[PDB]
Image (cartoon, coloured by chain):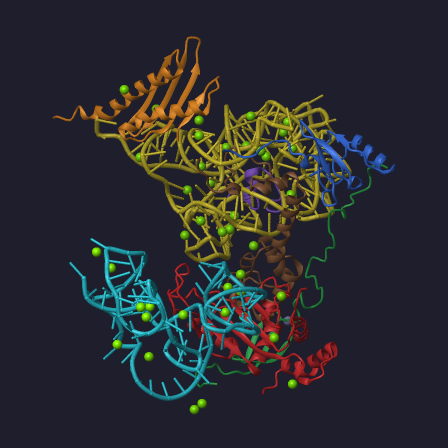
Chain colours: A green, B blue, C brown, D purple, E red, F orange, G yellow, H cyan
Amino acid sequence: MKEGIHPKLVPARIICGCGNVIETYSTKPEIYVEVCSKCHPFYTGQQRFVDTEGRVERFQRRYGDSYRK
Amino acid sequence: PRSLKKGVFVDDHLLEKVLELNAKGEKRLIKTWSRRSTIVPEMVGHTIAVYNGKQHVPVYITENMVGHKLGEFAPTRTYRGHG
Amino acid sequence: ARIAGVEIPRNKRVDVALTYIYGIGKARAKEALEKTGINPATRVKDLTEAEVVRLREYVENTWKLEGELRAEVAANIKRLMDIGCYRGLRHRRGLPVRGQRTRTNARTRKGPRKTV
Amino acid sequence: GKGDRRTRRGKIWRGTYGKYRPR
Amino acid sequence: PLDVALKRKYYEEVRPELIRRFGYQNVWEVPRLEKVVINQGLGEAKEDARILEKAAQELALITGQKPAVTRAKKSISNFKLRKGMPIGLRVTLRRDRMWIFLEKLLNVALPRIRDFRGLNPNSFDGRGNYNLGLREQLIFPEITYDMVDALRGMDIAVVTTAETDEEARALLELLGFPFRK
Amino acid sequence: TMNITSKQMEITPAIRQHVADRLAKLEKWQTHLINPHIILSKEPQGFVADATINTPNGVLVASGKHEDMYTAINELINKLERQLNKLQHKGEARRAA
RNA sequence: GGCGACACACGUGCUACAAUGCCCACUACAAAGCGAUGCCACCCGGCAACGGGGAGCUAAUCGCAAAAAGGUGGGCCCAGUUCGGAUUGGGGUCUGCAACCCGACCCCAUGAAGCCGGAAUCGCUAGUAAUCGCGGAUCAGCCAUGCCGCGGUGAAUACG
RNA sequence: CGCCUCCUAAAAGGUAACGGAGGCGCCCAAAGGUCCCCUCAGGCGGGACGGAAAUCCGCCGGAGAGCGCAAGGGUAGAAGG
Ligand SMILES: [Mg+2]
Ligand SMILES: [Mg+2]
Ligand SMILES: [Mg+2]
Ligand SMILES: [Mg+2]
Ligand SMILES: [Mg+2]
Ligand SMILES: [Mg+2]
Ligand SMILES: [Mg+2]
Ligand SMILES: [Mg+2]
Ligand SMILES: [Mg+2]
Ligand SMILES: [Mg+2]
Ligand SMILES: [Mg+2]
Ligand SMILES: [Mg+2]
Ligand SMILES: [Mg+2]
Ligand SMILES: [Mg+2]
Ligand SMILES: [Mg+2]
Ligand SMILES: [Mg+2]
Ligand SMILES: [Mg+2]
Ligand SMILES: [Mg+2]
Ligand SMILES: [Mg+2]
Ligand SMILES: [Mg+2]
Ligand SMILES: [Mg+2]
Ligand SMILES: [Mg+2]
Ligand SMILES: [Mg+2]
Ligand SMILES: [Mg+2]
Ligand SMILES: [Mg+2]
Ligand SMILES: [Mg+2]
Ligand SMILES: [Mg+2]
Ligand SMILES: [Mg+2]
Ligand SMILES: [Mg+2]
Ligand SMILES: [Mg+2]
Ligand SMILES: [Mg+2]
Ligand SMILES: [Mg+2]
Ligand SMILES: [Mg+2]
Ligand SMILES: [Mg+2]
Ligand SMILES: [Mg+2]
Ligand SMILES: [Mg+2]
Ligand SMILES: [Mg+2]
Ligand SMILES: [Mg+2]
Ligand SMILES: [Mg+2]
Ligand SMILES: [Mg+2]
Ligand SMILES: [Mg+2]
Ligand SMILES: [Zn+2]
């Protein structure tokens, strides 16, 4: 590589919020991120962050069967 | 919306013709003036004519239109814009 | 893109900041800081990083927010517009939905006046 | 102001009660 | 050649599963990565403030490599484009920096994407290469909210030695590329 | 803008446009015609064309009658012109010391 | 079913565009009215609308009832914001045979326009204007921000 | 009305008409000398904003691009970048 134009790559820590730490390389030796592949809901299986809903409507109402048959 | 303590309202005279069709191998076309009646699941799959004040509108009930009223599907005002 | 994907303002208190999130109002701001035991009057510039991911964790796991919320609200307006019910028609035309008079006003739904 | 239901002043304007104006 | 986990994962895990999935008879036949070409079609800096040096300072932090200036082929009146004008940045990543970039790309960048639901499975070259665009540059771990000024995305070309899209789908998915379909 | 009321009577959009074109004679005086309001009506002997218009210098109120509706309209404009030209020039009279 | 429609246009009003302000907690000070399938104390459940218990009062006795502005304390720090509360998604309550068209209210979320308004134009001469709440008729409920009343705080100016 | 290009012009050169069509009266301090390096237009597929067409990637693609300006000749094994 040409000299004096490229940011030097050094060994680097990456600390995600989920405690996962990656041993990679970067121009910054230590970086904090809010998410990573180890915890992101698309990555960690069908980790439905909230809406493990199912249908949900238009029948799980069932309030109720009091009308006659 | 209606209190949950009260029931899911159907005019009873419409609910009856639903089950007689269910318990015999439906369907015949149902004419009705019961805009106020809820679309209970036993109705799913029928086609019912709703009076809008002028015409009885054929409304095919599907699975995703249950917690609703029959009037919502036979609108009353003809409007096509201005100009 | 701190929490939750929205870079909430520093300089402001936590309860006030978290309102700058799609899905979190004054009510849910009280709920997040009690359930994680954070002083609701602490500026975002002063949250210990332990506090942040503590606050971040509870918020994102409890409630639907930003994109997932917006996709859902749209999906409900979409299904209303597909099943052809009356409210769906009002969304089809951009007219109001909750029974308001349209002979005048309704400028929020219609937009600024179109001359003739 | 008075037109805001989620405040005390709004519930006073309407004559109603709730979480933001208890009785 | 540095020891980077993605490169090691390529040789130790990825290659054996590829040989087994396709039955290659020569070690040079198994798909590998040729290069990763990052491109910014800036153009919002054509005349305005040709101080895209802001962006070159960014891509250099992201890749450890100084990007090079792309200049307009012909002149285009509707785009307000004079032949020769500087309209973006291309940086070509190979060998360890290519691995080092892709390593952080799969681990950190793609997860930070807004409402991320996986890479587009249909974006393949038809000859075994892949391409994806980005909407922002904060996606990367080195570019913080403080230092940024404007929202500039990029194109990323992933060039493999695979002759077909299927072999390339296999290689990239095995490296940790999250596809939705 | 200009409003037209047909009291206890139905008129066409053509008739309304004739009225707007006839009131356009008042644009001669190059003064703001503010919310002009015409009322066409039917009495047992003929039609009545009323009008109320405000200008920066005063208001105009006039009523025209005739068997023929257009003539009653025209008579209205004549009475409205004479008032407008009075509003626009009466101040010039007491000018010399 | 419509009278509630909606490319538009005008009249009357409500809430505002903020710091003489907004929010929360605590604490004062009225008048006139209404009230026996009525007004509801107080207790319990619910964040709440409300629900279940249940006393009192044919009512200067019991109840609607808390008046609000104000006072005290704390927050907000000039940003389309802790200004503003439109619009919409979702969840409930209650009346009523029935709330799709087309009810009011509560709760979560959404959080629009609006930065004081062109030509033009209205009211008001003193407890008035301005501002703050309270009550009643109609009334199952309510589209009342209307109307008829009631008190609280309380000005400016009139040469001519 | 002088000059350039093509045709008329009858396969050397030349060849007329108030015959058929276009251009010139500049320009360039590099658009000149040399050395080194590089190769087009276009089609298809892929890629945030981004489009028929901006920039990126892959495959095909001998010259249809380019060569300041008319036309012709020439030309990438460069006269083009
Ligand atoms: Mg060297
Ligand atoms: Mg050297
Ligand atoms: Mg919010
Ligand atoms: Mg309404
Ligand atoms: Mg006020
Ligand atoms: Mg508010
Ligand atoms: Mg090898
Ligand atoms: Mg493909
Ligand atoms: Mg390939
Ligand atoms: Mg980053
Ligand atoms: Mg009119
Ligand atoms: Mg005349
Ligand atoms: Mg009706
Ligand atoms: Mg009416
Ligand atoms: Mg309406
Ligand atoms: Mg009009
Ligand atoms: Mg009003
Ligand atoms: Mg006012
Ligand atoms: Mg300001
Ligand atoms: Mg805003
Ligand atoms: Mg604005
Ligand atoms: Mg606000
Ligand atoms: Mg709702
Ligand atoms: Mg209704
Ligand atoms: Mg004001
Ligand atoms: Mg004026
Ligand atoms: Mg007087
Ligand atoms: Mg009142
Ligand atoms: Mg009532
Ligand atoms: Mg010749
Ligand atoms: Mg010849
Ligand atoms: Mg010859
Ligand atoms: Mg010779
Ligand atoms: Mg000649
Ligand atoms: Mg010439
Ligand atoms: Mg040079
Ligand atoms: Mg090409
Ligand atoms: Mg293409
Ligand atoms: Mg695109
Ligand atoms: Mg393109
Ligand atoms: Mg050529
Ligand atoms: Zn993580």
Quadrant of the image containing the C terminus of chain E? bottom right
Q: Along the line of sight, which residue is nearer the eye, B6 or H53?
A: H53
Image check: G60 left or right of F17? right
Q: Position of residue A37 (x, y in %)?
A: 64, 71
Give the quadrant of the N terminus of chain E: bottom right
The residue lying at 83 percent from left, 37 percent from top is B26
Q: Nearer the viewer, residue B72 or G144?
A: B72
Residue G126: quarter of image: top left
Q: Is residue C82 visible?
A: yes
- Residue sitting farthest toward the top: F45
Give the image location of residue C68, x and y in percent: 63, 57
**Above/below status of D17 relative to C41:** above
The reply to whether residue B6 is visible in this rendering is no
Q: Position of residue G59 (x, y in %)?
A: 65, 25
Residue F37: x, y in percent? 39, 24
* Residue at 31% across, 25% down: F25
- Of residue B45 and residue C113, the one placed in the foreground of this image is B45
Extreme residue in the right direction: B24
G127 relative to F77, above or below: below
Position of C90 relative to E6 (above/below): above
Total label count?
A: 0
Splitting the image into 4 quarters, where does residue E173 fall? bottom right
